[PDB]
Length: 50
Length: 50
Image (cartoon, rainbow over all chains, first blue to last red):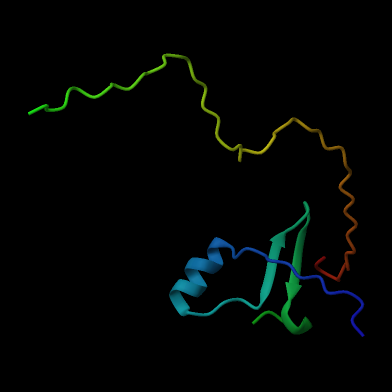
């Protein structure tokens, strides 16, 4: 049973926009963003950055 | 022949007028909202990250 689903929208940093998406066509699998005056990092699938 | 004359002429009544239309604009008033933003955040502090 689900006991809670925190769904959020984080922005893509500039160094990830120009270097990764516009250049290589890929995107990082981890989101490091400041939310509610704290810098949180979310790793996809609870795995390493890819 | 006995041909006709000028018409009777409209009897015009001078006066002042005020023209009212249906009111569709909402009634507006100044209100004041007192409330409290309660934000509770659950953070998992990892080895290197939060």
